[PDB]
Amino acid sequence: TAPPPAYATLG
Amino acid sequence: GSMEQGFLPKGWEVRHAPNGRPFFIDHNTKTTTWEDPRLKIPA
Image (cartoon, chains in turn orange, blue):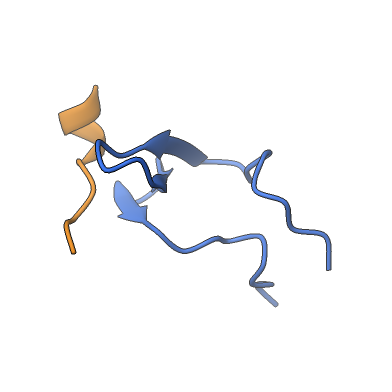
């Protein structure tokens, strides 16, 4: 239901 | 064949979402996926 955090978002 | 999400292919990372579900992160094209790349065979 929700999208996962982007690579730059989690870094 | 053998799947078992534990080890990932080159450029493929795995992380946990705040919801508790694990998601895969492809360093190559900066994309994220909830689908397992090991239970699906690229050929």
